[PDB]
Image (tube, rainbow over all chains, first blue to last red; front, side, top):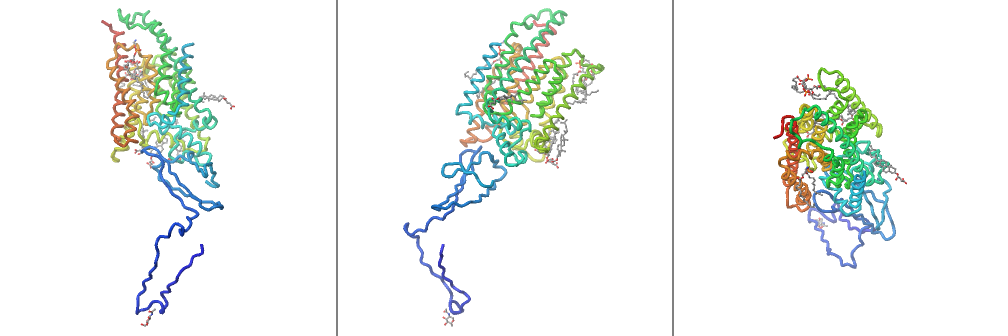
Length: 104
Length: 420
Ligand SMILES: CCCCCCCC/C=C\CCCCCCCC(=O)O[C@H](COC(=O)CCCCCCCCCCCCCCC)COP(=O)(O)OCCN
Ligand SMILES: CC(C)CCC[C@@H](C)[C@H]1CC[C@H]2[C@@H]3CC=C4C[C@@H](OC(=O)CCC(=O)O)CC[C@]4(C)[C@H]3CC[C@]12C
Ligand SMILES: CC(C)CCC[C@@H](C)[C@H]1CC[C@H]2[C@@H]3CC=C4C[C@@H](OC(=O)CCC(=O)O)CC[C@]4(C)[C@H]3CC[C@]12C
Ligand SMILES: CC(C)CCC[C@@H](C)[C@H]1CC[C@H]2[C@@H]3CC=C4C[C@@H](OC(=O)CCC(=O)O)CC[C@]4(C)[C@H]3CC[C@]12C
Ligand SMILES: CC(C)CCC[C@@H](C)[C@H]1CC[C@H]2[C@@H]3CC=C4C[C@@H](OC(=O)CCC(=O)O)CC[C@]4(C)[C@H]3CC[C@]12C
Ligand SMILES: *[C@@H]1O[C@H](CO)[C@@H](O)[C@H](O)[C@H]1NC(C)=O
């Protein structure tokens, strides 16, 4: 996104020198709902499915918020040895239908 | 026979109904019914791993032999049909084995009756064809309709397959067939290491059937024993070497036999090894695991000493000891030696402490799921509750087996010396 930045060159004597300190004050409050920026195109959350101390599921939700563009993603999972995984139970369901990863 | 067909039909119908029920998933995940070496989910996982190019023995989930993976590669479909067929085949093998054993023991009894070797008045202890008519049918009925076996086959555990192998070993041994008995014993030793202890009962029964005196000075005994031992060892070596080539690697030997002998999982079971090694000082871990795995093979020789002339009871006691002291015991393993109870039900009059032990076994079995749920899902119980249940269950099993052994000894003593 096109972002505008204000530069405070500390190497400039005309900005900060021995005669004064610099204290940048910014006025910012939470914008109203109308002025809120759009949600980022990619975000994800992770959680554990089920209850008890015998079995469960490590579920990851991957959100694509782009209205019309689909992009690949690369998911990396590292699970310790005491959480014995069964790869035959690995399901990737997007929009309610099975999704086949390009590379597993 | 018609009653055998009726029992087979009833058992198959019950198994199919439980297969199509909503309790199949609940049963499939029971720690009492499945084990790290026998779970069906692990078979599916090890089959799926091969599709990814990953050797199934590189992980810590798959612990089954290459023969199982070859069988279930072709037969991944119709798995429930496969397990129902294995249960029916075990029932058939046990039925015919016991039917032949009854004839053999009746011929022996008639021989010592003609020789008047028994006591003058032991008519009550005398076995009659009328009482032995339905023993083969009851043997197949105590296995097919056992709740343990029904659960073990609905959960789709390879324990049913290993039980079928042991049953066919018993049948072939009872029907002569030294070659087939050696092959089936090698196959049983392939799936689980412990069934190698049945070598002594099989050899003793074969020698008795072939009328070779089991004496140190005897040479025919040594010749036949050497042939049987060589046949068994060759059949096991050939199986190991052949199944090496399935994945062209030796990694299955650790994942199966080192798993069986070293107990790395420490996952709850009806056994006595899960907690002993979870709650254990690492100083004596090797010593105590060595002692506990010696325990299974400990009694075969002294039992052979006492039961030299009674090899089938020796085999039954050995099967029971294996099922009790296995590293990863299963209710399916326990159900194999409870199919022999109708054979030894003529020992009932000399059986003490039968009601209490049966009640204890029933209580422990019903209490396994309840206390497991309280510990794991409810959270209001510890592992101590489940450990206590396993202790009580195994004590009941041990006392029941020793009780049948005592009844057998009492009957032999009365037959020899005189009942009052
Ligand atoms: C399904 C998940 C959990 C279910 C748990 C159930 C599993 C229990 C399975 C096996 C446990 C059995 C262990 C001991 C087996 C004894 C073998 C046996 O046959 O001994 C027999 C003796 O039987 C007994 O003494 C035991 C009976 C006394 C108590 C049992 C009956 C009450 C229990 C019922 C509770 C449940 C009822 C529900 C509806 C049935 C010998 O009989 P016999 O020799 O034929 O008599 C004629 C004499 N010539
Ligand atoms: C292999 C031994 C040591 C242990 C397993 C027991 C076998 C003797 C049994 C158990 C399951 C049986 C199988 C169960 C199902 C079938 C399918 C059946 O054919 C079909 O129904 C296929 C139909 C189709 O494919 O269209 C042929 C027999 C077969 C292979 C059976 C052959 C004998 C098997 C392997
Ligand atoms: C069944 C009875 C009659 C013995 C038969 C002996 C051979 C058929 C087998 C049994 C054990 C096998 C061995 C078991 C373990 C290994 C380690 C293996 O090396 C590894 O990959 C390391 C494995 C590890 O230790 O974790 C090479 C094959 C070898 C020597 C095997 C070679 C073939 C052996 C000797
Ligand atoms: C079909 C039957 C007759 C096979 C008989 C062979 C087994 C008795 C052998 C074959 C492979 C052996 C296992 C190979 C590797 C290990 C790991 C080892 O633990 C370690 O990692 C320690 C290594 C070290 O001490 O340096 C403990 C013994 C054990 C389970 C061995 C126990 C004995 C096993 C199961
Ligand atoms: C194979 C049959 C015919 C022989 C009888 C087997 C048992 C009586 C004993 C003999 C040697 C023992 C093994 C010797 C060495 C080891 C390595 C040992 O490795 C470890 O230290 C890891 C396990 C742990 O320490 O808890 C595990 C036990 C084990 C497999 C032992 C298990 C019990 C065994 C197989
Ligand atoms: C830099 O120093 C001079 C001399 O003291 C001072 O007048 C000037 O204000 C200083 N710069 C800034 C940005 O204040």
